[PDB]
Length: 59
DNA sequence: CGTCGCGACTCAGCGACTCTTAATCGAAGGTTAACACGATGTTTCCCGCCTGTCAAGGGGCTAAGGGC
Image (tube, rainbow, N blue to C red; front, top):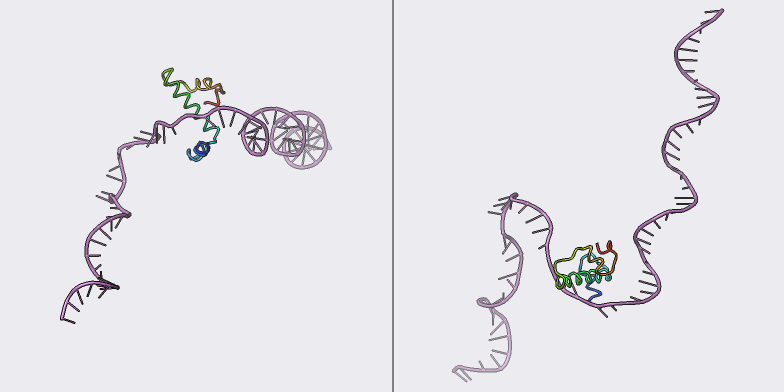
């Protein structure tokens, strides 16, 4: 928890927030699982509904 | 009358900064526990004060035409 709490801040050079880091990690994990099971890379508009979040927020 | 007890000695050894001078084209890949109030900003309208139209009215100044 401390590494994930600190890696999410002092790793991007811009100090991305912890919740945004976890959201982008969830997005990349969903994209990886889709590439592994479904097939080709999904569109960014599809990842918004794949995680049950706003379509504009994922963009 | 020898050496060794005890001292320096310089020799090796080990580390370490630059790669002329202008130029042939711009970006560049990964790492994947879950949730919760709280205090902290973010973003919309909504009136407050104020700013800017053109208009209406008018008068006052300027000037042009007519009469003696």
